[PDB]
Every structure is written in structure tokens, then in C-alpha cells.
Length: 291
DNA sequence: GGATGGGTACCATATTGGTACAAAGGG
DNA sequence: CCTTTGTACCAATATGGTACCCATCC
Ligand SMILES: [Ca+2]
Ligand SMILES: [Ca+2]
Image (tube, rainbow, N blue to C red; front, side, top):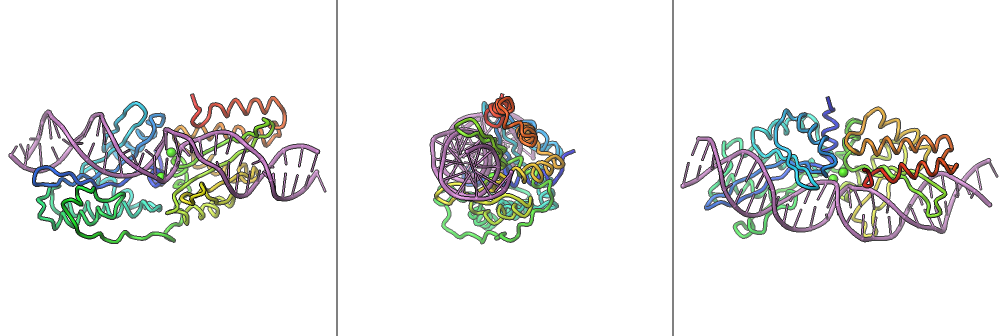
């Protein structure tokens, strides 16, 4: 019984709305897809999303990865109606919304293969142009025409429900325990990172938690980070929030472990060597180091 | 025959997510 | 003086994207 706002936040973080164009004799097939992909560690959270959407689509699994793909046109409408009731708020909103347009053109034609007779098709290709990466260079072989405007959405970014934040953070959050090189101090941090595109949304997080700060990820300012470090702030605001809007997936355990350490810091155990050794043990088994 | 579904191979970079310390700052 | 905090550093892979083939169905 997982929250629709959760689902949206998660697909604001992972999640794609794609239209692919596939040539086949004189005709081009228009293949749409909506996709979440993750590392196989978190297959279970994908199983859960998939049930949220009745049981549309199919999960696929290789060595390291797993993929949820919903490609069929009947299946895709269930999805659209969710995201219409529960709007994305990252730039991904604009790729979803081009995707809707294309879907509508296709429903109004009750088919998905087109003769280069490019009305319906040229429109689709113009739309598809300003979407994700955009045109294959072999669709640029067959078409030199123009691209429609991509809806802006820049202030259009108030966080809609805390649960959004829990799906999103379950996606792009990290829960980290720092130790000094001396091996004498220990500290926590909560970080959520994102492309420049959505700089404006991330800074809005500082309001959402009433703590932390916003900085740059890397010198070539291509990337941004929301970070909290003050233990005051982590123990009062960040932890209690997420106890009430649960994080889902493997990250949930990273959260439990993190907030286990948070407790030993509260009670000052981190300044005793047994506390310190104990924390270190928890650290060696969280995040990418788990199992 | 032609159109569609769907499995799986492949591609690129934005997250993934770890380490480090000088400058607080206060009891 | 001692410990916390903000800010920086950054290698690379878990994300986010895309193309091809064919075997059933219309
Ligand atoms: Ca993302
Ligand atoms: Ca993730």
C-alpha cells in the first residue's frame, strides 16, 4: 500500500519517458517506453512499483541490472493517468509532457507504423526531437525539419508532499558516515545531488527541512548538492522526518544504520573507543559496502 | 505479407558515494 | 585545545538513455 506521491518522487529521480523511432522497410515504427532501471540489489522496490501500476509492463534482469519497461499503448495510459493526478516537478515533467502529446497523436490513429508520409509522423519526429537526447543521426539522414519548444518549468517547483521527498531521496539520496584519517572523530552527512538544470529545485530543499546548505559538487560547476552536516539538524529534523515518511528499498537499511550511529553520537558514545570501534563496524557494511 | 511485442545488447554521464582538513567556536 | 562543520576533491558505476532481431498475430 505505497503512496502515489512516493511513486512520483521516485520517478522524478530514476525513471524515463522515451519515444524511440525504428525504421522497418518503407515504414517507421514509433516505439514509446517508460522506464525505471536499477541495480539488482533493489529488484524488490521495482516489483512494488510494478504492482502499484496494476501489473502492467515487465521487469527484466541481467547480471548487475534490472529494468521495468512499459512499452504497450494500453499499458501506458494507466501510467499517464497517475502522473496526471500526481505531477512530476523536476525537468522530467517536460519530457513526460512531450511524451503525452506523442501518445495522443498515436491514439488518434489507432496504429504505430507510418509511411514516410510525414504529417502525423513529422509532428512526432519534431516533438521527439526536443526530448531526452533527441533524434538519431539516421533519422537526421531521413529528415531535415524543425523542433518544437520544450515547456519551461523553473519556479514551477514547490515540493508537493513529504512523501514525494521520500520517493525522491530513496532515489538520489545518500546517507554517509565520515571518519577522520587519525581515526578519532566521526560525523554524519545527508546529501542529495543533481544536475545544474535543477539547481533552483534543490535550493528549495533548504526550506523543506529548515536546515543544511547547498553547494557545488565539482569544479566544472556542472552539478549541485544539498548537504546537511550539523548533528543538531540531522537528529532533530532529517531523522524524525524519515521515520514518519519511510524510505523504501536497500537504502532503508542504510538509513537505519545511519540513524543507529546518530544515536551513539547523541549519547556521546562516539567519544569512547568502544563506541568508535562499533560505529566503524556499521560503516563497513552500509551503502556500496553492504553484504 | 505486414505490424506488433518483447527480450536483450549497447551507449554515456549524472549520480554514486567515498576521502580530506582548515576554519570555526565555545566553556 | 578539542571537536564539530562547511566545503572541497573526484574515480567511476548505477543510472538513464537507445537500437535490433524475430516470432507470433492480423
Ligand atoms: Ca536522476
Ligand atoms: Ca539511486
